[PDB]
Amino acid sequence: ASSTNLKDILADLIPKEQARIKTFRQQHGNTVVGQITVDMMYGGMRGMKGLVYETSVLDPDEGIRFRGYSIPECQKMLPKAKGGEEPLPEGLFWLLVTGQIPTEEQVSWLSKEWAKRAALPSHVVTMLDNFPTNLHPMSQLSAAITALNSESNFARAYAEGIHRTKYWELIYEDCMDLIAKLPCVAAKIYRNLYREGSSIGAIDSKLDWSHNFTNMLGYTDAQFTELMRLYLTIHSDHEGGNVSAHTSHLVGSALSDPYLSFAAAMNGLAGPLHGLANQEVLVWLTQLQKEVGKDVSDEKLRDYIWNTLNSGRVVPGYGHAVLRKTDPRYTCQREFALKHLPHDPMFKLVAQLYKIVPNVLLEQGKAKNPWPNVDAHSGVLLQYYGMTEMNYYTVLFGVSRALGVLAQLIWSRALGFPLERPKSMSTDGLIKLVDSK
Amino acid sequence: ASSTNLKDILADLIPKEQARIKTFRQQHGNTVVGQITVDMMYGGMRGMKGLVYETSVLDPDEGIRFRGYSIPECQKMLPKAKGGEEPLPEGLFWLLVTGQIPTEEQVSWLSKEWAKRAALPSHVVTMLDNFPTNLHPMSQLSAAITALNSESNFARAYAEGIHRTKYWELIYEDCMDLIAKLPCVAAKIYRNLYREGSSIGAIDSKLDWSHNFTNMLGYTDAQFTELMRLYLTIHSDHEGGNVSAHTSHLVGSALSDPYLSFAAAMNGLAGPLHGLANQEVLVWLTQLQKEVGKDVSDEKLRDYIWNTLNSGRVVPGYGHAVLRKTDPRYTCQREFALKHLPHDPMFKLVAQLYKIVPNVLLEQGKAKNPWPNVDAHSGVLLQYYGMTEMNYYTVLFGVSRALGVLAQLIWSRALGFPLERPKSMSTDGLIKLVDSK
């Protein structure tokens, strides 16, 4: 056959980043990179630097980057799927871990490599098949990723006593297993929930990752698969600061093993201020599809959106405190839509708000980035291919953010990052602090 | 009957703290309360202020305080159990929430009030009875607190749309339920695991909280119960910064409901750098009980501990970067031991290290707080009353830290604290930052 052996590459890359951080930290290390205010400290840590998350940086002129490789260079560069046009999430985890762009057989590797590592302990399987259909997917996804922790290699090698400098090699092995069992768990949370408890199927070492998943979800549409490949590539990662990424991080720094850290991250992503906004827009988009009715003019939604901005509401999906042009991940799923559902009524709706909304905002003071998110485009693209079941959308973001959160988990463990322990305070403390002192 | 109605008190206290924070933040609010370094930011946030956690402050001269009420004022002040000598965890949650010291019928209230709220959905019960006995308690405790999330009031009232200023009243209701179902869940993780899957029993509105628990654990010793009452009071809370407290906080700030935030906190407390040190000492204490043998002299453990400090090891349980005298929570369980197991061989072991260790360290440079933790005393006190099963110790700390973590959860939600979102960075970012800029 063929390849190049991921672990063995990462094995090489490690000492070189490990040093780079040793000198940096030697020399300028004490160079003050900012201040904290009594107000930030009530402000949920409002624009504090405190992380070092080495897999993605928000570029204000250019969206998000998976190195400096942004959005638009990824779609080019990342291997596409042996007869497709949209990237493999495989080759994206590979980029996130390596810093390098996969080769076809570096990706063909992972796919083989995920299919085998893809197995499920009879007790998560049982645990799923009895869960109540009143329990949310995301309470199931996280209940069962903890219960998968039964199987961690790290838990065990820890228990036996591996040493500091070896931690990555098994935290690696736990991550590669998790990202393989993930499709199974969610494919089954779907199937039990929404496709009347049927069988997820089997799993095919022939196919790539996203495919197997879509195939277990029970979807025969190769257009949907390639949306699945695209969706999973683009919601992977987003700086370290955000709830699901900071929790997998925080918790993972107590030397908790990847099953447990990831499950704790979904408990953050099931949180309304975090998971639920892909929905929020679809729902808005839904009332609007009624209130302003089917095939509107450029004049009537201008009337609606205007009568919306000014009568003391907001347009779900639009605006960004930093990013200066349109989010590339809107643009990616738009480019998709243009190709594959161009004359869709509801995509027609979204694509109209794109024409109209920015100017309406910009002209009406709510501005500086009046441009759309990702979250604005996606749900419309899900509902088209018949994924109506919108509570379940939060799991699909979960299975995606997995690649980005676990691929930095190996790195915090490789560069051997400390237990995360900011100082708390208390108001009475503070009152004596800033002013009285 | 009799009482005073907790929710209704807290209802009163709220606006007054709510303002106090409005003015403080009005005026000095921008007063800079510290700086951040490139080095802190790799240093897992090494002595950053970033939290406001209003239920406990570390006093360096005086241990931990549950206001300014420290250790020693609590044992006095907190109601003791209608024929006991050790405080009720009931009256401690009450202190943590109110800021005020319970009255007997404020506590008698909670006990009644926990017993009724104490019920368990048939699906967590099933989920427990089939869990594998190879799955850790703490992967079970957290799997089933997520699955209890099926029952959150907040989840629902959120779903229906309560408004900002009402959030506490239901986040309250979810917390009071959780702390009542907790005994049931852990009593059953024990029983299934270690007491051959037997029945937890029933639940008695007559008895107080810790009692019911010990009674479901299946322990007939009223000395053990009162250890249980003491244990649960003292490991409740410990500033906000620590893994289990920061995670329940972080995650709970994405508007996740208390079941989900607490379950995510245990995924942090199951982490080796966090849960597992109560054990670590018992295990040390165990080898020593052999290597230096039964009834040693003040001269021979001096030899051991000295031959330990100098031959390049450390004494599990001893030392503290801040606290200047002996941790009161050593002293609390020592005072206990003195009373109730005075002539215990292994307590004799601990109490000897107390005589010997500090001076041996102090004289041998490893000093400034050479004094013992809590974690040093507890496990010895557990093993005596026949709680041999030491993997399960992490759940008993869980059920304790619950009171302190949930009682500040109501407060972050009451004072309406924002989604927690520090800025990440990246090394390449940093290199350009501190020096190049």
Image: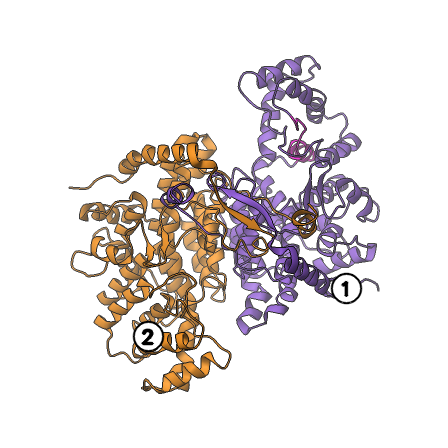
Chain colours: A orange, B purple
Q: Is residue A365 magenta?
A: no
Q: Is residue B86 visible?
A: no
- Nearer to us in this view, B402 or B425: B425
**Mark sitting on residue A118:** none
Q: Is residue B124 left or right of residue A156?
A: right
The answer to whether residue B382 is magenta is yes
Q: Is residue B79 left or right of residue B175?
A: right
- Please provide percent x and percent y for residue A166: 39, 32
Q: Residues within 10 Å of mark 1 (few under 14, many from 20)?
A: few
* Residue at 41%, 81% in the rendered image: A305
> Would you say B322 lies left or right of A330 here?
right
**Picture coordinates of residue A390, whole percent (x, y):** 41, 70
What's the magenta region?
B368-386
What is the chain identity of the residue bearing mark 1? B
Location of mark 1 (residue): B5
Asked if A237 appears above or below A367 in the picture, the reply is: above
